[PDB]
Image (cartoon, rainbow, N blue to C red; front, side):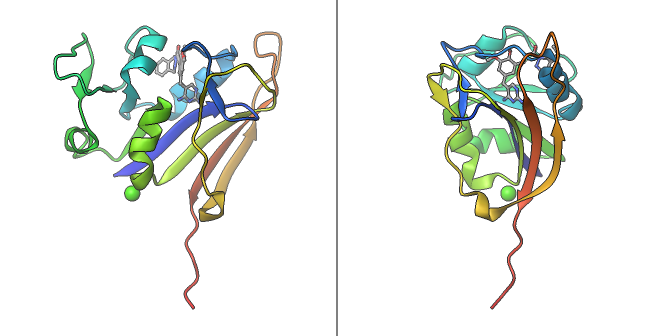
Length: 166
Ligand SMILES: CCC[C@H]1c2ccccc2C=NN1C(=O)/C=C/c1cc(Cc2cnc(N)nc2N)cc(OC)c1OC
Ligand SMILES: [Ca+2]
C-alpha cells in the first residue's frame, strides 16, 4: 500500500495554532477533498477533534493510545500495526496529521502531498523536518489566491528519489 503524508504548512512548517489552522483557505481544503477521495484518512485524536466531524466519503481512522476511545462513523486504531492491519487491502492511505502522527508513520512514508503557504503565521505545532534530498518532485501547482483564499500557496507532490548504484 502507498503511505502518503497530506499536509498544509507555512514558511516555518507551522501546521497548527491552538489546535486549528492559522489560515482559512477553502480552496486548499477542496484540494484535500479531491485528492483523498476514496482513500482512508489517518489522523490523531486532537487533529480529528479540531476538524469536528467525520469527513464524508472516506474511512476516517483515528489514532489514539486510549483503548476506550470511540466515535460514531469513525474507526479507531491504537498503533501503526493496527492501522496497517485495518488498511490491509488499501491502495493508498493519507496520514492527515498530528505532528506526532507524522512521526509515527515516517519510517513507512512513500509519497508527500505538501501545500506550502508563502506566509509566516503564529503557530505552536510543526511539520517535522525531512531530508528532501531523498525526495523527487513529480507535480507542482499554484493554488488559487482570491477574496476567500487570501494567501499565496502551492501544491507540491513528492515521491522517493530512486538512487543510481555505484
Ligand atoms: C470543506 C471541504 C473539505 C472538508 C473535507 C470533506 C470531505 C473529505 C476531506 C475534507 C478536507 N477537510 N475538510 C474540512 O472541512 C476540514 C479540513 C481540515 C484539515 C486539517 C489538516 C490538513 C489540512 N490541509 C492539508 N493539505 N493537509 C492536512 N493534513 C486541519 C483542520 O483544522 C486543524 C481542518 O479543519 C479546518
Ligand atoms: Ca513504504
